[PDB]
Every structure is written in structure tokens, then in C-alpha cells.
Length: 287
Length: 287
Ligand SMILES: Oc1ccc(-c2ccn[nH]2)cc1-c1nc(N[C@H]2CCNC2)c2ccccc2n1
Ligand SMILES: Oc1ccc(-c2ccn[nH]2)cc1-c1nc(N[C@H]2CCNC2)c2ccccc2n1
Image (cartoon, rainbow over all chains, first blue to last red):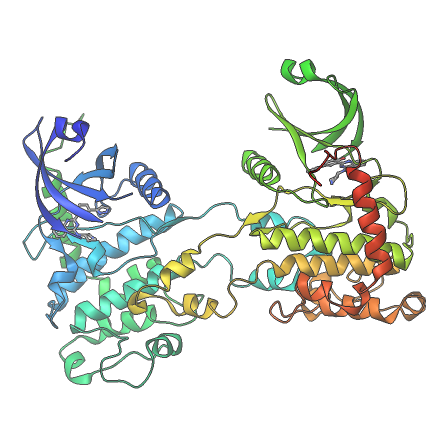
């Protein structure tokens, strides 16, 4: 059975995705919510919760309530459209302009995370949710269990004294330090590739090259027939995200200023979707 | 003034070293103790405390009591002999056999830390204490503020899925992962060098080469005149600890099985010092 405190406030309903996620209705409002159930662990949950509570962005999922019981119960706003994954499996093809709308929201979200010292670390189609079944909708990033919070490094502190006793490898690590966030940009790269093309850039399907070797070499599977129907600006951005060198890799800022996203129509549709979401919540304002 | 709870149990006394460390007497026993005062921070203290409470080794400092107040008060067993630092400053020279006795205890201590998933990260003469003013005494490692606890890596967890979305640099980091403890072995290397020779291997004294460059290149300042009076087994062990490559660097096990420490006299003197320390604490045993 469900905890009594949960039951007090919500009627539980069907399962939505896989911990697990159920549909529920909040008694007070009769409105639909999502409830994420994480079995008993605590670190991932405590951080996701601490993160989502402090974060505030249209393309980051918001937490509504939390229950610490025989299991963990996280109450989130519901995403009716489901996983981006479902839109790209079975070589299903997202039309390029839809890719742009989605990816643009993904970039803003991840930019926001990074501005705020958060690295997601597990970005993939499964963790990107669509706000409705419309093809033009808002997307929100979820599943912050694996994320990491940047902070005043032990490295920084170490650099404040004299390295009389300090090992060589620590000093060498200084060259590459502070680029952990770049792992999110690689992931977005892969996600964008998949969205545009309907297939994964790195894969074991019909290769003798190991997955590991394709990834470290940076050599994605380029299928001209499929990519031919895709713009050259799009593929160019993909190429700047799939850069092996983390220091050379495009950041979110560079991605956002890339020509492929200089698209005033797209930004309009997004702004449209925004105020539309917010219509029901808007208080009157001093004019 | 000192907190009332501290005062209740101890009479505070003179300062010993620099947070700060004072001499004190425990009222119950009239015995001397050391009290480490750390101003207000909490992470270093909570970890040192959590570490020292769970650790149990003749060459690791033991905690006696703790006070969480306007400041942090840690009550440790007193080390009458002071810092190893004082024995090596002003080009003062430790006689080789004393070096061996001390370093051997240092190796056991740090081996113990490593067996137990602890990395010290701040080993230097200042953090090595002598148990008495005798030249043949026990040493104990202190100052565990900067230490790190090894645990089930986020890296390990990441390796359990498919890296479809996983950045190249994470995969590359696998080659070198799990050798963080080697930074302690470098430090011991430097400490041993200084003990044997009376001077630092890496230094800005009379060089145009940057400190950073000497360390990453591995090129210590070798002064034959000073080292001539030093055994060749000793210098050999030093050389195996000052290895730039962390994977090639001697571990504590390798250091302990190095010929320079195959010295039955030395181990005897150490065992002697042990049972001697413990004489006052020994309960009778079933024979
Ligand atoms: O509607 C939601 C609201 C919030 C969250 C969420 C926030 C933080 N973690 N999960 C998830 C859902 C959510 N999650 C789903 N599947 C998972 C698989 C792992 N990635 C998402 C899902 C799947 C199908 C339909 C609706 C869904 N709604
Ligand atoms: O007698 C002690 C017992 C325990 C500890 C300790 C344990 C954990 N942190 N510090 C230190 C002392 C201790 N510490 C000293 N100086 C510091 C400078 C930083 N490194 C040690 C010291 C210096 C002179 C004479 C006695 C001393 N006793």
C-alpha cells in the first residue's frame, strides 16, 4: 500500500514510465500530477530534491511535494506528452524544425544548469519530457539523480599553498580542470544527432569498431542518404558538439549563437508556448 | 573565554603549535592532553573527526573528546616530542637510521589509511608528530582535515550502462582512475628526501626553473656532496617514490618491501617502543 500521508493528499493512478512514475490526482485541486517513486539511494534523491527545489526554469521540471517513507515519493508537475525517446525510436524521424524547437529549449535548460553550478550528467531522450501531445510543445529536463554540484574546489585550495610536497599529477590536472560541464554538451550533441537522423552516432550495429573506440576517436557513423535530407547548418552544430577535446567542444552559449538557432520563427513559437503555459497562473500587474 | 563544557573537564594551558593547539590537563586523571582549536570549516572538521573516531593504529593520532561550540575543540593524546618539521629545518640532519625508524612508521600509517579507503593529501613534516623528546620514539600522523574517503565511484556506476551518450573524456579517465592514493606516496618521497639530506628536492633556491616545472618533470635538486654521506639503498627508495607517473610510482607495500627497510634492528626498536607505550594500558590475558 501507499503511505497514509501520500494518500491523504492524492489519489494514485496508472503507471506512466520507468525507479517508477505514476499518474495521480491532487485532492485539493482535482488536477493531474506525476509521482516519482524511488525504492530504498538517499544521496541521489536528496540532491535531486535539493536541486529541483532551488531551480526555477520553464524547461526544468518543478517539484510539487515530497514523501520520505517506506519508499521515496516525489510529486512533480505532469508531462502529458511523454518521453522524447518515444519520438525517436524505431528510426522515427523528427522534422528538422521540430528538432530545432526542442533542442533550443534543451540548450536554454542546460545553459541555466551550468550558470547555476549544476551538471546533469545523464542527458538522453528518456530524460527529456514533452509537455503535451502537440508537436509544438514545451520540453522539460528531468532525472537529476546523477547530477553534480560545482563548488570551491579542493584543487583551488591546494593551489593556494606552495607545492613543495604536492604530486606532479595534481599540477597537471590544472590544465583541464573546470570543464566537467562539457560532458553535458557532448550528450546534447548525441541527442541532436539522433533527433535529426533517426539513428545513434555511436553504436555497435554493423561495425567491427568497439563502441568505446568510436567515442574516443570521435568517429560517428555518417550515413549520407539519411543526412542528405537534413540541413547543413544543423549537421555543422552537431559537429561542433561532438568534439573529443572537452576544451574545444562547443559550450551551450556557443551553441545558442550558432547560425542554426538564429531562427526568429522558432523563438516566436517558443515564446508563444511560454505565455500560453503561464496564462492560467498570471496575476495582474501594476501598469 | 573557553566554553563551559570544555572547562568543566579540562584545565587549559600554554600553546604548542599552529588552527591552533594548546596543552591541557584532564581533571579526572590529571594527565596532559592536547586540544586542537579550529575557528568558525565544518566539513574538514566533521571528516577528520569521523575519520579519527573510526581509525585505530599506533602511528595515527587518536581523538579523546570533541566540543562543538563558539569554536571547534578537538581533544587529542599529547605528543611531547613536537613536529618532525623542527628536526629538519635549518638544514638540520637526521641520522640515516633515525630516518629509517621514522619513515617506516610513516609507511605503516599511510598503508593503513590506504587499506581503509582514506587518502591524507597533506603529508609534510609539520603533520608528523614525535611521541617524546627521545630520538627513538613513536611518530603519529595528524591533521586529517584535507583527507578524502574513497567510495563506490560515480565512474564505476557510469561504466555499468552503455556509453551511447557518454563523453570521450570520461572513458579516457578510466585508464588512470583509482590512483589518487599515489599522491600520498609522492609526499612521503619528498618527506624522506628532506629527512635524509636536510634540504627540499623541489625548491626555488638558486634555480631559474619554476617550482611547477621541477615537479612535473620530476627533476629534483641532487647535491652529491650532501648525498654522498647517505646510503645508496635510501636514495634508491627515494627515487622510486619520486616517480612522475602515478601508476609506476611505488605504493606503500612496495616501499615496505624495499631493501632499505629490510632492517631487523630497526623493526625491533619499533616493536620495543610499541609495547613500551602500551605497558600502562595492558590488561591481563587468558594464558
Ligand atoms: O511527468 C513527469 C514529471 C517529472 C518527472 C521527473 C522529474 C525528475 N525525475 N523524473 C518525470 C515524469 C515522467 N517520466 C516519464 N518517464 C521517465 C523515465 C526516466 N525519465 C522520465 C514518463 C514516461 C511516459 C509518460 C510520462 C512520463 N512522465
Ligand atoms: O600533540 C598533538 C596531538 C594531535 C594533533 C592533531 C591531530 C589532528 N590534528 N592535529 C596535534 C598535536 C600537536 N600539533 C602540533 N602542531 C601542529 C601543526 C599542524 N600539525 C601539527 C604541535 C606542535 C608542537 C608541539 C606539539 C604539537 N602537538
